[PDB]
Image (cartoon, rainbow over the protein chains, first blue to last red):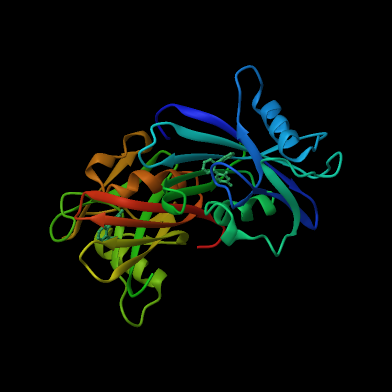
Length: 158
Length: 156
Ligand SMILES: O=c1[nH]cc(-c2ccccc2-c2ccccc2)c(=O)[nH]1
Ligand SMILES: O=c1[nH]cc(-c2ccccc2-c2ccccc2)c(=O)[nH]1
């Protein structure tokens, strides 16, 4: 139970049997970290459509099916709006990922995921993604580097 | 996590009710609580839980199930508390009042959280869903949680 208005975001992870696709954020907020593909959900699209849109804007990739794998709520200290991130997964993709102004994509082997160069929360919830366990997460950050509080639980329904 | 002291906490958890005890004196007096305390040299953690349950409620138990581990840090106090949380449905006997604890059943929709340790509001949901967990709580005095973490786990 997290009270107050929340802004919808998506995050997509292309997770294949032996590898995961990440993008190096090139500009803006969180520039310099590897990340899934995502952003704010817009007025007039569904959450899944927002996810597809962000993936295609940032990597050129289109997808057959996206699967809901988690929801993460973020509080940032001093910022009034909570973020409600819907996390999606796909295995099969259509096309080869291409570099955008926002993101430089690369494939990573599942034992070489660069956690020290990713958002701190990823170290906690990525293992659940890898083990195919649906989850709800909560992280309170102070700035970009410090997790002050967090909760993580497995769920039946995302 | 640096240096720490082992503690147990036991929740008798039945389908419609949970047995708590009102702590009659000493530390945390006036709060409803699970049963437990310090683990002694030469006993296992579960044997200490069983011991404390019996001393405080009169109850003996068929099986105790590991539900979680919670680490407590109190600002000022140097040593951490490493609390092992246990659960049990089937019990042996009536609970009875002791010098440390007056037991009382509470219906699951009337758990008196405002008269319990504030951390209980956070981790009881996982207890009640039969999930296992690792928790951490930083306290300033007896009322104030400064920060915490709580992660569902597969093994305690
Ligand atoms: O793995 C991640 N965790 C958190 C963030 C993040 C941190 C701060 C602000 C916004 C986000 C954000 C942006 C877009 C889509 C989802 C989340 C992130 O980018 N990636
Ligand atoms: O539900 C609870 N949460 C925290 C405490 C607690 C708080 C402060 C000091 C010690 C404890 C303690 C005592 C004995 C056994 C385990 C924990 C508690 O008693 N009960």
